[PDB]
Image (cartoon, rainbow, N blue to C red; front, top):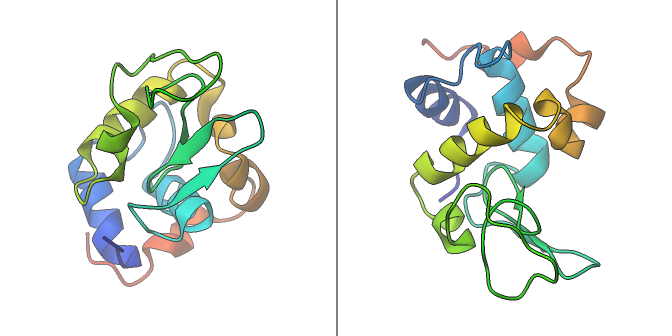
Length: 129
């Protein structure tokens, strides 16, 4: 499923992500734009055999089990295919675990490179929330 900006903003807000561990909603919508371009099915097959899965491109070496990643851990206790569904819940629940462990939203390179330090409010422009 591909989400539009406001549709995803709304769904993320429904899932309690606004101000989660100090990160306002615009951060999460900015991170999903540059990680996956709002696509729940995006996958990026990496160098040491891990793959990033879903709207928020969560990595299989530490967070989910896909059965083929070299020294993998399954900290969110899920199959990586749960992160590829049209409904965002397994991705937001694993993302809340990531931000609570590894240094806030720095875990997402696209947030850290493209969103960090900009005015993220813009990403909720025009969405009545």
